[PDB]
Length: 202
Length: 397
Image (tube, each protein chain N blue to C red):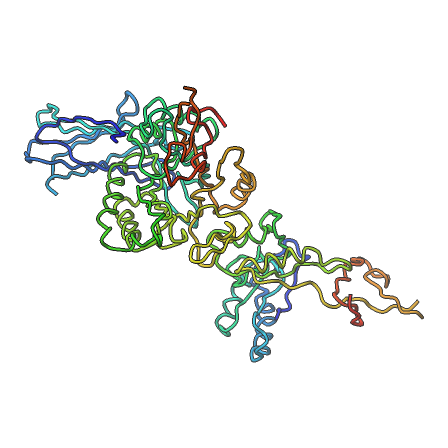
């Protein structure tokens, strides 16, 4: 389960999740989810958001969740995905062997991330293997690493269903952002499904 | 035979017995203090005095004096400022002189030992030398001479150190025994991290640790380890004590590791046996662990080095006990190996086996290099004794 928190476009990323005036809203959006969905046994890992920037509100909410329901590990990908606000190290698009050392949010090779000093938490890939049409490449490489390394425990192929809206010319044709006259948009970046919108297998 | 020098030493009735010179530093290494703990023997007179003087070359920097009182042991602490630290790049040397002198000042006996200022400690999975991570580009220097067997002399030792430093080798592992006493002195003088290795090897015994678990061999193993430690503690070049090469992990190795960590806590202790990951080892040192290929042997597996790094609950650093066999036109995968060493922070290099070719000169009268089995010896191991980066006469391979 993933709490509805996303402030990617804000500059910097954690300009909001460190201001303690947004603790009420973030706490509502996290605690209501936890309370509503605690009983179900399928839900195993609570996630406080996708790269929303690591401030202090995320530490507070992580500790609140670990105090309320200690039967589930809490993952959170922001702030380099290795902060104290995360039990399950979940980076985004960390490549297998190639290293991507970005400032303050680097993308280590996953094996190097495993071999980081003082690091003992398991690693699952928050997002990996973008399925953009004829894509899902390096999957094997990825699965080879997953099977070799015990503390690397797989990832989440992004994403399942294609976010295509039906447009009529009257022949239906799948459309993306910007085909409705919307601006600004992000063209075909909304088309990353393992199956089509009507569930025809890719 | 008698393969090392025989000497005759004369001492007065009262003499200096033992002294250990340790060092500690502050956070920025600007301020440090020297512990020249000293012991003596014989009749104890109130007028007896000891003096520890620190000379940076011809100039004296720090000194101290104290009478006895253990009634035969006296502790001196000498403060040093902005010390010239010691590392393989810069072999800074301090000539500390210990004096056994009379109350009026007449000198009875004086002893000295070269002392370097360095720190070796383990934290967060990294081997820190003077606050910095290390890159061990080692080598296993076997003691062998083309025309004298295992008789070693200063010319050969100096020339080997020269060749070793000319090729960016800044680490040596005496394989598998403590070396000649002057070797360590030359190592301090030139700058070369040494990994001393206690003379313990029982590879052929079935099983490997049938001897190193029987507590009837604890006396012999303790002698062979503790005498080395006591003799070679003072030298600053020796950084890592090694209890042996894959001798099988019993209980004697745990006992001796704890004894070493109790006596000289300034040096990490490595030991390769029993999978090289037991409690009897601070520096995980497997043999021939390949970079990516995995070799899962029963009870002594050879993981890929990266997998060994990523083992659960494992935080100790990894240096390769032996790797890159240099059998003639060999040293392959070196790069692969060095790529892994440079990528992975907690992987800290290895020891290229081995330095000098163990070839004995045979005359047909033309000298021709020979191996095991060419002298009529049986059983032998043919050309497996030929794994040198240089020939026996030091012609570069």
